[PDB]
Amino acid sequence: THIAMSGLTNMQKYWLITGSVGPRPIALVTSLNSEGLCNAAPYSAFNYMGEDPPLFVIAVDHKDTLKNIIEREQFVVNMVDERIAERMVLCGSDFISEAEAVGFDLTPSTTIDVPRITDAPIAWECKLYKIIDFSKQRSMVFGEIVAMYFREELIDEEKLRVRVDLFQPYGRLGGPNYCRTTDRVRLTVPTFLPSAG
Amino acid sequence: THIAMSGLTNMQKYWLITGSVGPRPIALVTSLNSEGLCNAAPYSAFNYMGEDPPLFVIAVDHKDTLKNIIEREQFVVNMVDERIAERMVLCGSDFISEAEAVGFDLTPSTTIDVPRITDAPIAWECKLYKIIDFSKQRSMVFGEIVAMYFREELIDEEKLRVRVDLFQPYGRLGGPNYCRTTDRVRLTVPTFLPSAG
């Protein structure tokens, strides 16, 4: 089946796009407003872009997240596993401080002023690299990772490796659906090259 | 545990980043070179950015993918499920036409010249929107979705909805690990707002 994008409404495009790219990683962004109030909002139009400098992108609609990031040039990306999944979804509601409304405790960050979520498995302490406006209603936030927090069980500090087996983030699928990362396979890139043709 | 990025090598940053953001969606990009040869290469530094216009981003290293996209201003994003996962991983090898070497058959696209992978569950027919150079060795490719192909079983054509239950893409985790999307939960955003504090 083929479907052209030209025939569709923005809602139809949204459903076909979000239903066909997945599973998506979830950035639960904590940020601070003018008054020191902490906002929290999840975004799955999100991925890393590179390691030198260590940059990622989040697409955000014009929620207070964008203004907080613009003003402070700092924010935290909290990664999402079972321990915070429900409250994460509650943060996506149409609300004030989400972190207070949904019951997230906050823990100070080391390199920046914006706090992380206490129960987060992993958190990136980030500075604003650049905002590219997508449209008058949407912006691409490029963040630079300046440091990372890990629950001790999730990091091999001597090896500088995430313990991949133990870290079990939720991925976003189409609709209100999430994939748990509990069913895995190892597929290695061989050194011995195929040449079937 | 806290780890600053300033202390690390590029390899260490790569491992901590790719181990802490996941699961990631996989864009298996097919593209054409000067001679009509089809290259195929998977990328998980990838996500959609918006629906109006329908744009996505893939971060790519300077593989022939980038030159093919620059020259033709067209390419296909093939989504990845069980049926093509192994060959997808084989395409990531250090090779010539990957599609031939690994045994992908190709099917013509409707709106563009670059073909899709015959066994792909879903494919985006794409035009180049813009390339932003990250560095001399890395570029962010912004693509516009002009049309989509779905296996008939995966699309509710009357409703214009992906059948989310049946579409089971692989997500990328840290290391050579993949999460199958077989263990899901539905978590809805309530209309009834929490106000715990």
Image (cartoon, coloured by chain):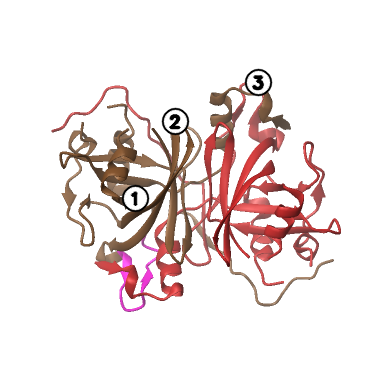
Chain colours: A red, B brown
Q: Residue at x 41, y 76 (%)?
A: A9
The residue carrying mark 3 is A158
Q: Confirm whether the magenta stretch covers residue B10.
A: no
Count every numbered label the image shows and give the total: 3
**Left or right: A77 in relation to B43:** right
The amino acid sitting under disc 2 is: Gln
Measured from the top left, where is residue A27 in percent x and y?
61, 51
Query: Can residue B76 be seen in the rendering of this structure?
Result: yes
Say whether marks 2 and 1 touch (CB < 8 Å).
no
Q: Residue at x 58, y 67 (%)?
A: A137
- The image quadrant that residue B90 belongs to is top left
Which corner quadrant holds the N terminus of chain B? Answer: top right
**Left or right: B25 in relation to B41:** right
Q: Residues within 10 Å of mark 3 (few under 14, many from 20)?
A: few
The amino acid sitting under disc 1 is: Asp
Which corner quadrant holds the C terminus of chain B? Answer: bottom right
Q: What chain does badge 1 belong to?
A: B
Q: CA distance from mark 1 to mark 3?
A: 35 Å
Q: Are marks 2 and 1 on the same chain?
A: yes
- Span shown in magenta: B154-167
Q: Residues within 10 Å of mark 1 (few under 14, many from 20)?
A: many
Q: Confirm whether the magenta stretch covers residue B158.
A: yes
Under tag 3, what secondary structure? loop
When the figure is inspected, residue A113 is found, relative to residue B166, above or below; the finding is above
The residue carrying mark 2 is B137
Q: What secondary structure do most residues of the magenta stretch adopt? A: loop
Under tag 2, what secondary structure? loop
When the figure is inspected, residue A9 is found, relative to residue B4, above or below; the finding is below
Q: Residue at x 77, y 56 (%)?
A: A104
